Length: 182
Image (cartoon, rainbow, N blue to C red; front, side):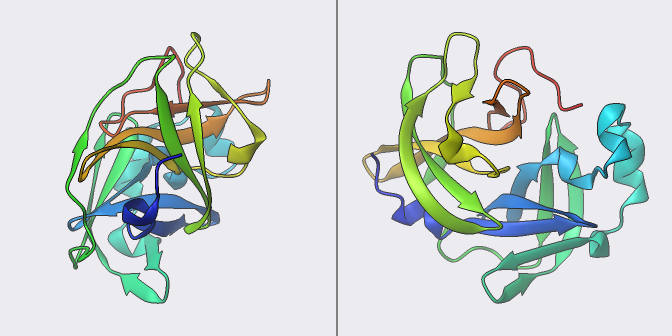
């Protein structure tokens, strides 16, 4: 329901090896789910600390349309990866990070490979999941609310559960509910 223009100008494509998903570009940092550094066999019992050390900056390919962002640093904050790039996003809006509760509504900008596809109003169920096919294949899409001119990011999609529901974190990397990225 919220207009998505301010958020569209922050969405990017993040690729590591064969994995490609959405990232959020604010200032000179790109936020994305940390399981992007995982391969197929990694996602069963991943050592995220060992994988972080194994990857170099040039293992990360970040694209904002045709502009290519050069990764000059990468750190991990809970379950989100933070990629420092060599350029600040000139379209960075006024923003803050907030943590919400189930039952509260927010708008989700569903993207695929960095391209905005739709915006939808939804809410987490009491078990901290979201039911909706609109998000299938949208790893890294973010949820948000607009407080006048400020964009409050409150959600990042991380994974689809076997039961067709979706799990995610806040922008500090803390999962909503008891879920784990393994």
